[PDB]
Image (cartoon, rainbow over all chains, first blue to last red; front, top):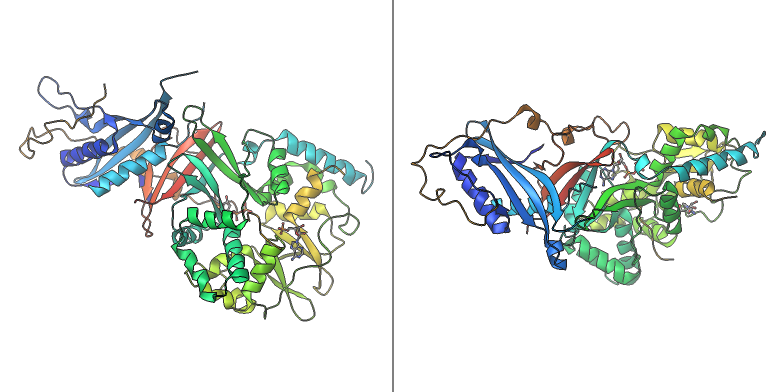
Amino acid sequence: KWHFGVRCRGDAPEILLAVYRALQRAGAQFTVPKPVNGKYRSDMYTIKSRWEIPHCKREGKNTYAYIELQLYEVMPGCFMLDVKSNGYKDIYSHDLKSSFPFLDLCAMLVCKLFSA
Amino acid sequence: AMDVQETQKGALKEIQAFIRSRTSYDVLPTSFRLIVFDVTLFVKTSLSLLTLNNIVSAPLWDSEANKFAGLLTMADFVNVIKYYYQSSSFPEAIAEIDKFRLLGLREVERKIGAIPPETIYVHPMHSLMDACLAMSKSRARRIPLIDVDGETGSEMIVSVLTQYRILKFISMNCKETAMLRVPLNQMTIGTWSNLATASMETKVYDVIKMLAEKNISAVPIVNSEGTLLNVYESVDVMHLIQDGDYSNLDLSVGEALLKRPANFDGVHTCRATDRLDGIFDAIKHSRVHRLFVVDENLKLEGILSLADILNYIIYDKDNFESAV
Amino acid sequence: QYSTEIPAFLTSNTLQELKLPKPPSLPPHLEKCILNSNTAYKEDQSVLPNPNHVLLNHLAAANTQLGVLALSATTRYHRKYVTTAMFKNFD
Ligand SMILES: Nc1ncnc2c1ncn2[C@@H]1O[C@H](COP(=O)(O)OP(=O)(O)O)[C@@H](O)[C@H]1O
Ligand SMILES: Nc1ncnc2c1ncn2[C@@H]1O[C@H](COP(=O)(O)O)[C@@H](O)[C@H]1O
């Protein structure tokens, strides 16, 4: 029953679109493809996002969460959208890796992918 | 130092020293699962999730703040039921529970007296002694290990430590358990009078009132002659209410004990002449939650509980039930 | 270099169209999730095998039939591993 990421079906860039819009609805910010003169490079399905962490926003602390997404073709027509955590960093100083708020954010994202 | 009760005396000394020198971190397996619920989950859902994952408890997460939001245990249910039975002139009012989200169950409890303002918890890198003192200061039988990620201020629920898993840890790590050779009836340990007991004829809600009133986790069932037959645990209450049938509470104990899945840690017994060395061994290899002390003919004499044992080693020589 | 706006070309739209690249195929290690491992109720049902230090912090998901979200990630706490499994509402 447990599996990495979330399943997707249909058209590869159709799914890329939905993920992008879903980020936009969460208020995450994201990298974007850049072609090779032409000409879109397969790494377009590698998205680095940055998320303002709400409970820190509530204090008014500028602490961010870094989340990388990656699409993989699984069968033809089936995809895993893989989500991984690059950690959290506040704009200040001065060494735990909690799954939170990373898991609370994947929760948000998944709500956006579905309410679409 | 060189005979029973002087050898035990010294043996206990090493065991507490062992306890202080370890951390809660140390008790944990090197790779494990932790199940966590959102505080806003509905009560029915959370009951379905305990059973389905085969657990009796779960730490709650308050996800908007990123903060530990309390510990969910069968005690929460036992306390609300007691309250409704003692206060409501309306037997079907208990059904109301199902509408609550865990957060609103916890408010009813808060309002009702059944909960500390202060949540018990400890840092996992502090001393294991810290965990015991707390679990015995409040009579909680499990405790969250909570740390804080300083990059976010969010809390990190690392694990929940039970009394059972502390004792198992001690059983597997301290050679000196084998030197506790003093029979129970010589020491001062367990309860030996005023036992809350019940029979098959007894009604479940009466058993639940006993559990809440004495802050006990279980109640022995005896026959007319007082031979030990079985037990009714606060975890047993979970199996009656799991489908929303809050009228299963009017069942007799016997009827309700038939609804029990095999699965069941069993009932453990010792004689009064038994010593702590054998019990740590029972613990080493099996899931004991308490020992009923009985005679030749299985007649109940008293109860030796996990708190009882922990308390005996860690210390130098009507209302409400704690986290279960 | 971050950004707030939806790339334009993903609205052209959108069949026609570039005939753009595929994503890479699923690598063999995301085929298996250690949560599917309960060798351990013998007797500590929380024990998992050691994870694989590539897969620390990758979200995994699971069907509940209960109308909530099941999420999890694995992380190192000092020298031990905690796989947390979150059950959560949608609203
Ligand atoms: N919230 C939880 N998440 C994951 N596993 C749990 C949880 N609660 C209990 N368990 C597991 O269930 C099993 C039974 O434990 P439990 O009945 O809770 O107490 P004990 O530690 O006395 O066995 C143990 O293997 C324990 O690790
Ligand atoms: N049925 C009972 N009647 C009287 N005392 C009990 C009973 N069960 C447990 N106790 C005692 O109350 C304390 C709490 O037990 P427990 O909550 O099972 O750890 C321990 O000191 C037990 O010895």
